[PDB]
Amino acid sequence: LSQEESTLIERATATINSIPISEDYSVASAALSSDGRIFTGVNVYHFTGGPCAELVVLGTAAAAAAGNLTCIVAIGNENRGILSPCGKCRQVLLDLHPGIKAIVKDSDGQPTAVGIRELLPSGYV
Amino acid sequence: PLSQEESTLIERATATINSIPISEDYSVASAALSSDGRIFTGVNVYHFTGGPCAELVVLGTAAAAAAGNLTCIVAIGNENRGILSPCGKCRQVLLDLHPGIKAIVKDSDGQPTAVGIRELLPSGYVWE
Amino acid sequence: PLSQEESTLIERATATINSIPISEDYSVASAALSSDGRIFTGVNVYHFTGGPCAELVVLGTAAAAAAGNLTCIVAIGNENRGILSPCGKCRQVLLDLHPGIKAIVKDSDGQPTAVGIRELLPSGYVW
Amino acid sequence: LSQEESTLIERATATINSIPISEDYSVASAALSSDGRIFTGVNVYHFTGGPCAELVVLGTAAAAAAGNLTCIVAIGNENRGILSPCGKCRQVLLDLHPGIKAIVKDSDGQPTAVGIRELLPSGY
Ligand SMILES: C[As](C)(=O)[O-]
Ligand SMILES: C[As](C)(=O)[O-]
Ligand SMILES: C[As](C)(=O)[O-]
Ligand SMILES: C[As](C)(=O)[O-]
Ligand SMILES: [Cl-]
Ligand SMILES: [Zn+2]
Ligand SMILES: [Zn+2]
Ligand SMILES: [Zn+2]
Ligand SMILES: [Zn+2]
């Protein structure tokens, strides 16, 4: 991982570890913008489709007029570490920030940043 | 009429949606008040898979800050649409996660008014 | 009191959920009535990404049958939970796609009653 | 594809072509259960997360106590043909029917059945 990738992991980790343990708010995300800012958020769990942390990040970035996001990561509570984006988040990320990379674990459990398109092969169009 | 703090929510959400490019994806801003005095903002993320409304982005932003219970929320539309009542999905999430919250809606006169979330979902479904 | 058709909806949704294995993923059934008199049923698909409630599965089932306008809907929970009021998300989709629809809910005395969808979303969201 | 798989495409195509053209009801899906039954459905578009056709199929199959679904396909209206499942559907399919395959188009535009895990690499 690059310096900025490690930094996103640290920011997301600090975010989730800094709030009370909760079944409603259990994952944090951090993303980097092309204009030199970092946005965080936590999920809102709900059966009607409450947003993942990544989507909260996207809305937070949009509220700040941070156009292009270039890298994103999700970190689970209780020291779970890096979580790969769920399929819903992958679709929203592909559609709204097609240039973005997401930090996921490789087969060795080692963090790596992968282009969003690679996380949705034979993508829906 | 509205309390001072309630008016501040309308101001803040109006500033937010007037501070971002006009967009079909990012078209509504929201602001909520915590019992701790802080205000949290958010903009929606439109998507057919169920991208969050602005209110849900606010909820996640407040949660990220370990906010004290939220007491009031408002949504403000782009293109100068003004106050928008929360959609049914947002109403359900607010009822379930912040049952004490009020939402700012327009009365009969088009005048801002704070209403308990329960009033916005009569015979409310209870997520157990 | 409910019409014959409305009672039939309750019976059909109840039969549907009672007929399947108890499950955390599939835990509510719904039945709706179309203006032409047909009945469509469905069960929910629970998922954190926003899997559909039974009502929405019923909407897609009716749509697959070119059912047109739906006039009444009800949801019934598993394990003899009985009538459940539609959640806020279902209310919004129902109002938007079938504005003429009523939902069966329990009134303040616990008695089934058919209510216009608009009444279930006061000061509703309009674009 | 196998003949059972080809039938899914036929059934989903018939379903979407049988209904009035609509912006709300625009995709049909068909799935095969382990015992050979076929279940169909159409989407319900809504900004709050109305279900894709696949999820309607999942609830339809569940209503019939179908158990495991082994194959699924989505067909777009207006002769759009096979549509790869979106990321949301991929996630639900993975979680509720991990043994399932989805029919997608290959490089030559020809139908191919792919395991759901391959459609969500490094899957959550
Ligand atoms: C890694 As996730 C559950 O926030 O899509
Ligand atoms: C007023 As709304 C579309 O953010 O629920
Ligand atoms: C009564 As319901 C959880 O199907 O909206
Ligand atoms: C191919 As789709 C829009 O039903 O996931
Ligand atoms: Cl959703
Ligand atoms: Zn996600
Ligand atoms: Zn909403
Ligand atoms: Zn519902
Ligand atoms: Zn889909």
Image (cartoon, coloured by chain):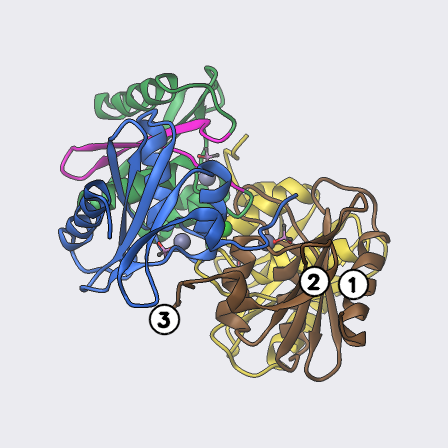
Chain colours: A yellow, B brown, C blue, D green
Q: Is residue B99 left or right of residue C48?
A: right
Q: Residue A57 carries which label?
A: none
Q: In this view, does A29 lie to the left or right of C11?
A: right
Q: Which of marks 2 and 1 is nearer the N terminus?
A: 1
Kindly tell me whether residue D50 is visible in this rendering: no
Distance in Å between CA atoms under marks 1 and 3: 32 Å
Please, is residue D45 above or below residue D79 in the view? below
The part of the image, by quadrant, that contains residue C22 is: bottom left
Q: Tag 2: residue type?
A: Val
Q: Which of marks 3 and 2 is in front?
A: 2
Percent x, y of residue C6? 24, 45
Disc 2 and disc 1 in contact, CB within 8 angstroms: yes
- Cα–Cα gap, marks 3 and 2: 26 Å
- Amino acid type, residue under disc 1 in the picture: Ile
Vertical placement of residue D74 versus C23, above or below: above
Labels 1 and 3 share a subunit: yes
Query: Do marks 2 and 1 both belong to one polypeptide chain?
Result: yes
Instruction: Name the subunit of mark 3.
Output: B
- How many C-alpha atoms fall within 10 Å of the one at disc 3: few (<14), some, or many (≥20)? few
In the rendered image, which residue does mark 3 sit on? B128
Residue D25 forms part of the magenta stretch: yes
Q: Tell me if residue C41 can be seen.
A: yes
Subunit under mark 1: B
Up-down: is C26 above or below C3?
below
Q: Give the range drawn in magenta.
A: D24-46
Residue corresponding to mark 1:
B10
Q: Circle 2 is placed at which residue position?
A: B74
Question: SS of the residue at dot 3?
Answer: loop
Instruction: Tell me the SS state at disc 2.
Output: strand
* Disc 2 residue crowd, few under 14, some 14–19, many 20+, Cα 10 Å: many
